Image: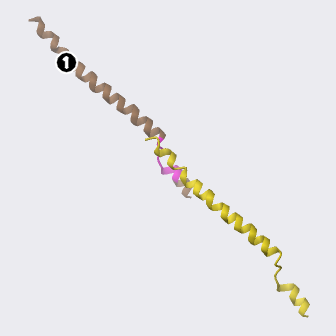
Chain colours: A brown, B yellow
C-alpha cells in the first residue's frame, strides 16, 4: 500500500529541474525585450 | 519404552549446527544490502 500511495502522490525532480531552468530563461529574455520596447518611442522626438 | 520416547522428542545436533551457520550468514549479508539501498537517494541531490 505504501508503494501504491507513493506512485499516486509523490513528486519527481528531473522534470521539475528542467521546468525551472526553462522558465527562468524566458523571464530574462522577456525583461530585456520589455526594456527594448519601452525605449522605442524615443525616435519621434528627433522629428521636431 | 525409553528408546521409543527418545525417538520422538530429542534433537539432532547435526542438523541444528548447519541451520545456525546458514542463518547467521544470510542474516549478515542482509544488512550490507540494506546499507546499499539507502544511498541511492543521494543521486538526486547532485542535480541541484
Dot 1: element: helix
Residue A38, placed above or below residue B5: above
Point out residue A30 in the picture as x, y percentages from the top left corner.
30, 26
Q: How many marks?
A: 1
Point out residue B36 in the picture as x, y percentages from the top left corner.
59, 54
Occupied quadrant, residue B34: bottom right
Residue A37, placed above or below residue B18: above
Q: Quadrant of the N terminus of chain B?
A: bottom right
* Image point (48%, 50%), residue name: A9
* Image point (27%, 24%), residue name: A32
* Image point (67%, 61%), residue name: B29
How many other residues sit within 10 Å of disc 1, few (<14), some (14-19) or many (≥20)? few
Looking at the image, residue B7 sits to the left or right of residue B21; the answer is right
Q: Nearer the viewer, residue B14 or B7?
A: B14
Point out residue B17 in the picture as x, y percentages from the top left corner.
78, 74
Occupied quadrant, residue B9: bottom right
Q: Which residue is mark 1?
A: A39
Say if the magenta span includes residue A11. Answer: yes
Query: What subunit carries mark 1?
Result: A
Q: Residue furthest top?
A: A47
* Image point (55%, 54%), residue name: A4
Say if the magenta span includes residue A39. Answer: no
The residue segment tinted magenta is A6-13
Q: Nearer the viewer, residue B7 or B31?
A: B31
Amino acid at each position: 500500500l505504501s508503494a501504491s500511495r507513493s506512485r499516486i502522490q509523490d513528486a519527481d525532480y528531473a522534470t521539475e529541474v528542467s521546468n525551472m531552468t526553462r522558465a527562468q530563461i524566458l523571464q530574462q529574455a522577456g525583461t530585456s525585450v520589455l526594456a527594448q520596447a519601452n525605449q522605442t518611442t524615443q525616435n519621434v522626438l528627433s522629428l521636431l
